[PDB]
Length: 330
Image: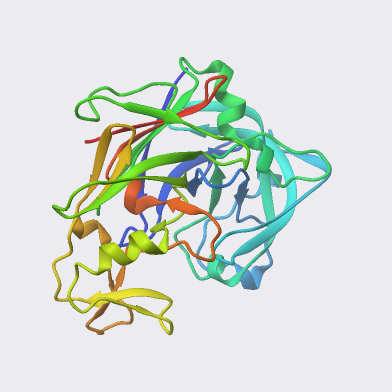
């Protein structure tokens, strides 16, 4: 089997991407944030504290003839950005772009933190990291990909995120028309439960490539590109007037600037992030100070190849016995 679904930016800055997901019988369609940095499929629901729902589409398990309460099961998660959610668990039928899993753990939110409430465009998350990170207790549950894997034509999914435009998540096949040149594959460590790999270095604009190992994770659920302070300083040094602002919480730059590109290495291959991808607009409405899309990972404890980096590539998440990551230009 295979699946193919379109993923759409939630706003004009590509702050995140939503993908429609069918849950239950009859189908209830929710727009979820496909997140290769976590491993819980959770949804706004009829069980969510009413005051914490503000415009999201909810899952109502009592209206699904295939929903079954997973007795005694609870979940609770906190994300790198400080957000959190928790609740109970159902199993139900879940389909993504024509690909169907029966008995998928659907984690129903009783509580969500304010950032989720305040974002009406995201109805929940669909985790695509390794199932070892799943928070359901006392019986850990598998991710959607893990549940589908054996049925897929090939045990892979691919992320093709758009810049200021829709993209695609495919399951079970590699669309050879979706990229240019070849796919370069690189080793993955699953020891932290992430799609963790090692970039071979970087360049700023037309500058010379610096060969240097950068360990980090391929994370569709993080907006920006988070890299070591040395690297990030090297980048913003090329932008007149850019500075790290403690009060804003990162590097800012004059909105009148033209940003240089940023290149990262995948083995011998190179992925070029155009400068425009690194502009995330005014820090506050009407400001002429703009927020940078490349930021320091110092204090996160891990480097994150988030959407800013991933949207410049066609990315293969290969879930073979020994997982690997593939990157191609597009």
